[PDB]
Image (cartoon, helix red, strand yellow):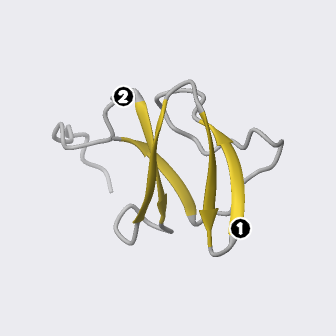
Amino acid sequence: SGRENLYFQGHMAAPARSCVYYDGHLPATRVLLMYVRIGNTATITARGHEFEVEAKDQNCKVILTNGKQAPDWLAAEPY
């Protein structure tokens, strides 16, 4: 609880200018859907549901270009 100590610089999602869409509730159970270039749109079909996304920024939120919010299981991380 109370020990102000630093945390190691660890492997995190690095802004690699591509958003990689995964079906994953966690960054562990993630299933590789596709790689989208930052600044491009992509129809993500998962479970027979198409999510038209736009890889807005290299933080890689899953923001649908159709105006929707995606399910919690739909993740994106920069490659």
Residue placed most toward the observer, 35 or 61: 35
* Disc nearer the start of the sequence (2/1): 2
Dot 1, crowdedness within 10 Å: few (<14), some or many (≥20)?
A: few
Cα distance, mark 2 to mark 1?
Answer: 27 Å
Residue 57 x/y as whole percent: 54, 26
Residue 14 x/y as whole percent: 31, 33
Quarter occupied by the C terminus: top left
Residue to which mark 1 is pinned: 49
Q: Residue at x 34, y 67 (%)?
A: 28
Horizontal side of 10 relative to 69 (left or right) equals left
Q: Nearer the viewer, mark 2 or mark 1?
A: 1
Residue to which mark 2 is pinned: 15
Q: Which element carries disc 1, helix, strand or loop? A: strand
Q: Residue at x 28, y 42 (%)?
A: 12
| Amino acid at pointer 1 | His
Q: Residue at x 51, y 37 (%)?
A: 60
Q: Residue at x 72, y 44 (%)?
A: 64
Quarter occupied by the N terminus: bottom left
Q: Residue furthest bottom?
A: 47
Q: Which mark is residue 39?
A: none
Residue 59 x/y as whole percent: 48, 32
Dot 2, crowdedness within 10 Å: few (<14), some or many (≥20)?
A: some
Position of residue 46 relative to residue 13, above or below, is below
